[PDB]
Amino acid sequence: IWGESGKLISTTA
C-alpha cells in the first residue's frame, strides 16, 4: 500500500 493516512482507500498492491 502507497498513500494511506486519514482517507480509507487501502486497495493498492
Image (cartoon, grey):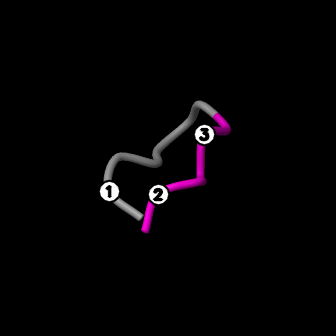
Q: Which residue is mark 2?
A: 12
Q: Which residue is mark 3?
A: 9
Looking at the picture, does residue 10 appear above or below residue 1? above
Indicate the amino acid at tag 3: Ile
Q: Which residue is mark 1?
A: 2
Looking at the picture, does residue 9 appear above or below residue 1? above
Residue at left offset 56%, top offset 36%: 6
Q: Residue furthest left?
A: 2
Q: CA distance from mark 2 to mark 3?
A: 8 Å
Residue 10 belongs to magenta span = yes
Q: Residue furthest right?
A: 8
Q: Main secondary structure of the magenta part?
A: loop
Looking at the picture, does residue 8 appear above or below residue 4? above
Residue at left offset 35%, top offset 46%: 3
Indicate the amino acid at tag 2: Thr
Q: Secondary structure at mark 1?
A: loop
Over which residues does the magenta segment extend?
Answer: 8-13
Q: CA distance from mark 1 to mark 2?
A: 7 Å
Residue at left offset 46%, top offset 48%: 4
Residue 13, how many percent across, how many down?
43, 68
> In the picture provided, is 3 more to the left or to the right than 12?
left
